[PDB]
Image (spheres, rainbow, N blue to C red):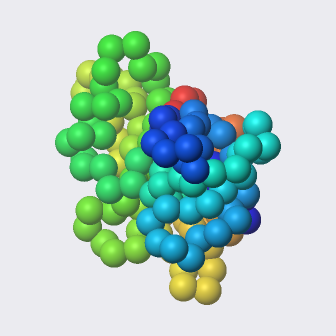
């Protein structure tokens, strides 16, 4: 598995690699602990890096529309920021049920003005992810790919992260 950087980091030591968010790496050694020996695929250089600054190249963690444990209110402030169009969205963890997620979208209703909708994304122990309309996806990336092409039940189609 390759890894990708989620934040910009200024090489501390000389044995420390310096890097920008978005850079990929191959893990040479990950046994000493919080710091890992790695090889940048952009420069080919070798050196250490904080393990909590990167995530697997396929993980949800590094997708840009995923905001881990964000709060309803927090995501509502984030999405409603001037400039964000209708369909802007984000996915966080469920604040109510353990092991599920919430798809938060910025939408425009006639009665309500400009607002946010929050749909729960359920999961089957031995099946896929699905939202209330009951169509499942093996992956949350697929799920997103899908509602990006067409609303298909949701109030709005997925536009921008």
Residue 7 visible from this viewpoint: no
The picture places residue 119, in percent across and down from the top left corner, at 40, 53
The quadrant in which the N terminus is found is: bottom right
Image vertical order of residue 87 relative to residue 145, above or below: above
Question: Going by the picture, which residue comes out furthest to the bottom?
Answer: 126
Horizontal relation, residue 119 to residue 65: left or right: left
Q: In which image quadrant can residue 30 be found?
A: bottom right
Q: Is residue 128 left or right of residue 92?
A: right
Q: Nearer the viewer, residue 100 or 21?
A: 21
Inspect this view and state whether residue 8 appears.
Answer: yes
Please state the horizontal and vertical placement of residue 130, each as a whole percent of the image: 55, 65
**Residue at the extreme front:** 14
Question: As rendered, which of 132 and 20 lies closer to the eye?
Answer: 20
* Along the line of sight, the residue nearer the viewer: 62 or 26: 26
Q: Is residue 43 above or below residue 57?
A: above
Query: x and y percent of residue 65 in the render?
Result: 51, 42
Residue at 39% x, 31% y: name it: 106
Is residue 159 positioned above or below 18 on the image?
Answer: above
Does 72 sit left or right of 83 as displayed? left
Give the residue displayed 61% in from the left and 86% down from the top: 126
Q: Residue furthest left?
A: 73
Which picture quadrant has residue 129?
Answer: bottom right
Q: Which residue does the image show at 42% across and 20% down from the upper left? A: 84
In this view, the residue in front, 2 or 160, is 2
Kindly identify the residue that appears in the image at 76 percent across and 37 percent down.
42
């Amino acid at each position: 598995t390759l890894f990708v950087a989620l934040y910009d980091y200024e090489a501390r030591t000389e044995d420390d690699l310096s890097f920008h968010k978005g850079e990929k790496f191959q893990i040479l050694n990950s046994s000493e602990g919080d710091w890992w020996e790695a090889r940048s695929l952009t420069t080919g250089e070798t050196g250490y890096i904080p393990s909590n600054y990167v995530a697997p190249v396929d993980s949800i963690q590094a997708e840009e529309w995923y905001f881990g444990k964000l709060g309803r209110k927090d995501a509502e402030r984030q999405l409603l920021s001037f400039g964000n169009p209708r369909g802007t969205f984000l996915i966080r963890e469920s604040e109510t049920t353990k092991g599920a997620y919430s798809l938060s979208i910025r939408d425009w209703d006639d009665m309500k003005g400009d607002h946010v909708k929050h749909y729960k994304i359920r999961k089957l122990d031995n099946g896929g992810y699905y939202i209330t309309t009951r169509a499942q996806f093996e992956t949350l990336q697929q799920l997103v790919q899908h509602y990006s092409e067409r609303a298909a039940g949701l109030s709005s189609r997925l536009v921008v992260p």
